[PDB]
Image (tube, rainbow, N blue to C red):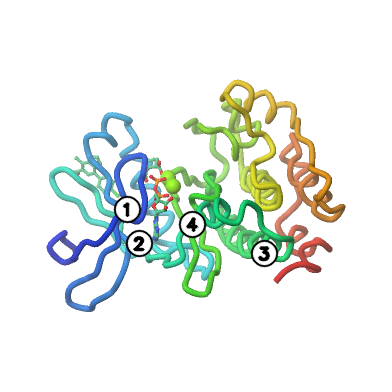
Amino acid sequence: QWALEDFEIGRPLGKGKFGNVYLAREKQSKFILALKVLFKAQLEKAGVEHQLRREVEIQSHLRHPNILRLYGYFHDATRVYLILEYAPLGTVYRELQKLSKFDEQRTATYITELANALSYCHSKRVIHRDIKPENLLLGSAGELKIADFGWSVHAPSSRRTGTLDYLPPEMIEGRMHDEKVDLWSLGVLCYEFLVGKPPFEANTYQETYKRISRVEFTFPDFVTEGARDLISRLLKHNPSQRPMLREVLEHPWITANSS
Ligand SMILES: Nc1ncnc2c1ncn2[C@@H]1O[C@H](COP(=O)(O)OP(=O)(O)O)[C@@H](O)[C@H]1O
Ligand SMILES: Cc1c(C(=O)O)cc(-c2ccc(Cl)cc2)c2cc[nH]c12
Ligand SMILES: O=C(O)[C@@H]1CCCC[C@H]1C(=O)O
Ligand SMILES: [Mg+2]
Ligand SMILES: [Mg+2]
């Protein structure tokens, strides 16, 4: 059992939907970590308290070098506190903003780390459902770590939940979905890492929705044939058509540019 009194709080690491994440140090051990602070009132207002227990329950039981660790949790009269592994090199989101786009080698490496973490996840029938650059953190060696299990569930799920940019058609239409949702988000990520923006991006939610439903996207000329092949294979309206993660890892373009 932990209390807030056990940690020295540092700077904010990032903004959340239901609070903020802070850098922190555990007083007795000097263990540097991240504290994801959530407000009870806002969670209650949204009726997401059940889903927060699920984020904790799912993430605490995962052990993989490419998945962010959740060490524990505690709560007080006003807040819920998630004790996370601190990712010192920040988000893939911030790296993409400064670099504009990644080269094929950096993209393929990230796709490999993601595919390994996802393979491990799906082995436990865990669907992340919120795979996006702001939820992909970087370890001390620059290795990708899947974070933010806030929308995580066990497959299959029929459970409903913007922006729609990373969501597959079946999730967008409120239909039943499985592990294939993360294979779709992988294709969206691969495209965004190479192009600098996701394939269904738009000025409005309405326009993005139509693009995802139609699987309506085009590649800029600089996107190679091997990158086009893997992305096109991953972005299939039909979840059944989406390849297994094993095939993603053995894709010629992945093996040639990773790691
Ligand atoms: N362990 C961590 N180390 C470093 N930065 C983090 C960590 N966890 C979260 N962040 C930062 O805080 C942001 C919000 O955290 P996240 O868990 O994704 O919250 P939410 O569910 O509100 O989206 C992230 O996008 C990232 O910028
Ligand atoms: C009022 C209250 C309690 C409580 O006192 O039992 C617990 C939680 C809560 C704690 C931990 C986790 Cl992981 C999830 C929910 C939440 C969330 C919103 N209101 C809450
Ligand atoms: O961790 C959270 O802030 C939330 C818990 C409840 C479900 C949604 C989730 C999120 O936005 O990631
Ligand atoms: Mg997040
Ligand atoms: Mg979240």
Decide if ligand 1 comes within 8 Å of the CB at mark 4. yes
Identify the residue at image location x=73%, y=68%: 258
Residue 182 in the image: x percent, y percent?
A: 62, 47
* Residue identified by numbered label 2: 84
Q: Whole-Å distance between the Cαs marked 1 and 3?
A: 27 Å
Decide if ligand 1 comes within 8 Å of the CB at mark 2. yes
| Quarter-of-image position of residue 74 | bottom left
Residue 141 in the image: x percent, y percent?
A: 52, 75
Mark 2 nearby-residue class (10 Å; few <14, some 14–19, many ≥20): many
Decide if ligand 1 comes within 8 Å of the CB at mark 1. yes
Q: Whole-Å distance between the Cαs marked 1 and 2?
A: 9 Å
Which type of secondary structure does the marked residue at label 2 adopt?
A: strand
Name above or below for residue 107 compared with residue 223: below
Identify the residue at image location x=44%, y=51%: 148
- Please tell me which residue lies in front, 166 or 170: 166
Q: Tell which tag, 4 or 2, sits nearer the viewer.
A: 4
- Position of 25 compared to 247: left or right? left
Q: Whole-Å distance between the Cαs marked 4 and 1?
A: 13 Å
Query: Which amino acid type is shown beneath numbered disc 3?
Result: Arg
* Residue identified by numbered label 4: 91
* Residue identified by numbered label 3: 106
The disc placed on residue 63 is none
Answer whether labels 4 and 2 touch (C-beta < 8 Å). no
* Residue identified by numbered label 1: 21
Q: Whole-Å distance between the Cαs marked 2 and 3?
A: 26 Å
Answer whether labels 1 and 2 touch (C-beta < 8 Å). yes
Identify the residue at image location x=51%, y=62%: 145
Query: Which amino acid type is shown beneath numbered disc 4?
Result: Thr
Q: Tell which tag, 1 or 3, sits nearer the viewer.
A: 3
